[PDB]
Amino acid sequence: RIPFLEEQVRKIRDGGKLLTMDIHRLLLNEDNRFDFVNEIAAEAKQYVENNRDEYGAKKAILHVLSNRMNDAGVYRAEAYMESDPFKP
Amino acid sequence: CIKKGQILADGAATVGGELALGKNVLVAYMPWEGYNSEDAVLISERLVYEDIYTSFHIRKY
Amino acid sequence: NLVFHNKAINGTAMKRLISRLIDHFGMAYTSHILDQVKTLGFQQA
Image 1 (cartoon, rainbow over the protein chains, first blue to last red):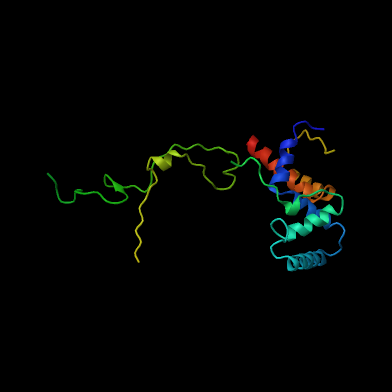
Image 2 (cartoon, rainbow over the protein chains, first blue to last red):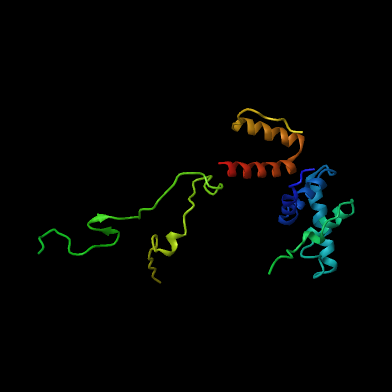
């Protein structure tokens, strides 16, 4: 338990390094890394065909990845969007 | 008084009858926060508001 | 649980350390480890 470790944790959560970990974690259950890409693209197309404007927070691919990470027991933000509350 | 072959007027990139293509600046050689890891220079802001490396360019259309 | 080093670390040592960390931790951990090593090296230099 290192005391001075919250800064880099906040940096990871803000800069967007969570997605780089989530992709690598999801690529641990699939044999081919191409069928996974095809499946994600198909799911994103099916989700954007239903509601055009309501594809998620900002995009659909991030929304699909957040939905896939939230169904495995890992709480993730909606389409990996977290604005800065300290912006004047 | 002047003689044949002596300078009456100066020119561009020349001062006192000698080629002048640059300026003299105080320079230190040291690593600085990785901004010069490759071939790169971290300059001071004095060169911007003191009109040191200011140049003119004329294009035609 | 990394090996404690008390000797000089040249380029080959860093290359071997990265090659072992990629096999022991993976590319995800190794990316952040290399970023932090870069930051510390720039600060020290």
